[PDB]
Amino acid sequence: AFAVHVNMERCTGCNNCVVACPVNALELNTVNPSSTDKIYKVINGDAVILDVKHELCAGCGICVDACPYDVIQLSGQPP
Amino acid sequence: EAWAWGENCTTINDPVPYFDITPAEIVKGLIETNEYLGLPHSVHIHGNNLGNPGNYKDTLDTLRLAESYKAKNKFGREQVLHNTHIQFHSYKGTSWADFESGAKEIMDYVNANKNITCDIGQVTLDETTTMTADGPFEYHLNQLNHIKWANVDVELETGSGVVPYIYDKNIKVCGIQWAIGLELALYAKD
Amino acid sequence: VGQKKLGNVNIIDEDCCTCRWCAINCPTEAITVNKIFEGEITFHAEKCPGGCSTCVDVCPANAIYLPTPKPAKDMKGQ
Ligand code: SF4
Ligand code: SF4
Ligand code: SF4
Ligand code: SF4
Ligand SMILES: [Zn+2]
Image (tube, rainbow over all chains, first blue to last red; front, side, top):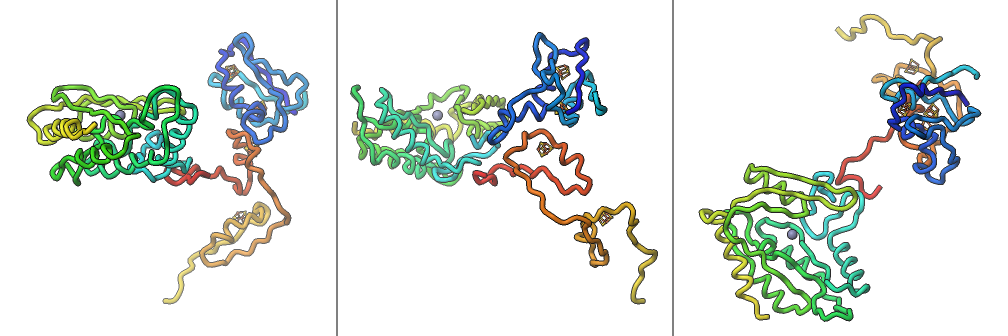
C-alpha cells in the first residue's frame, strides 16, 4: 500500500513501467484474474499513477528497476 | 513452426513442439474443413522431407491422406488436394551419389487416384533464387552451397527462406533434377 | 594413517535459520538442524503474473525457484 512518485519532467513515455508492474500484469496474464485495477497508464506521454489512494502497490521495485532513465522514486515510509 | 525453434518435421508422423499435433492430423483437418466449406480451390499442399533423396516414400505417405474424401462444391473440381512441385518430392535413393528418380512410382499412384491432381516443378537449368515459405529446406540448401540466405519468420503463422542457387548443366544432380520433371509429365495418362 | 580432519566445522547458532540445505546436502550426514516452524506452504502457479520474481529475490532460504523452461522437442504439450 506504498506510494510511488513519477518525475514527469524526465518521463519519456517508454511504457516499460506499465508493462512491468506485476499489479498491472494481473488482468491479462493470470488465470481467473483477481483484481483488474492498474497503477500506471501513459497519458499524454508521461506515466500517470491511477493508484491515487495508495492501495495496490506492493513495494516490489519491478517498476523502479524497469524505467531506463531512473525517474520513479519508491517511498517505503507511510505517506 | 518447429523451425521457429530450429527443428524440422522430417516425416509425416512426428509431433510439433508443444502442440503434439502431427502433419498427418493437420492435413486431414484442413481437408475436412475445406471440403466442408466447399471452397473453390482444394487444399494446395507442399509436403514434407522436401529436397532430399529417398522422399518418394514420404510423398506417397502424404498423398495417401485423401483416400476418404469427395470434392463437394457448386464449382466443378475433382481434386480434393493438390500436390505441388512434385519433381521436388519425387526423389529416390540415400544421398546425392546414389540418387535416382521416383517419378514412375509417384505417377503410378497419381494415375491410380482420381481425387489427386498435381503439377510439375520442371527445372529450367539456369541461375535462380529459390523462395519457399519453409525455413528448414532453405537453411539446408544454404549449408550445402555456401551462398546468401535470408530468413523471415512471421508471428504465429509461417516461416520463409530465400537462397540463390545454380541449376547448372555441369552437375549430375542438376541433370537428374531436370530429367525428373519430364519423366513425371511424360508418364501422365491423364 | 587413518584420518586427517585438519580443523573443525561447526554452525554459528544465532545466524542459522533451520533451512536444512546443508544438512540435506552434507556428504557425511554430520549436521543436525531442526526447523523452528512446521506447517505447509502452497504456490498456485496459475496466478503469478509472470515477471515478478520478488518472492524469489526475497526468500531467505532460497526455497523458491523459477522452474526452468524446457527446450523444444521436450515440452511435450506441457
Ligand atoms: S512497486 Fe511493484 S506493485 Fe508497486 S507500482 Fe511498482 S511494480 Fe507495481
Ligand atoms: S518507465 Fe520511466 S520513463 Fe518510462 S513511462 Fe515509466 S516513468 Fe516514464
Ligand atoms: S545451511 Fe541451513 S542449517 Fe546450515 S547454516 Fe545455512 S541455514 Fe543454518
Ligand atoms: S512475487 Fe512471486 S508469487 Fe508473488 S506475484 Fe511475483 S511471481 Fe507471483
Ligand atoms: Zn513449395
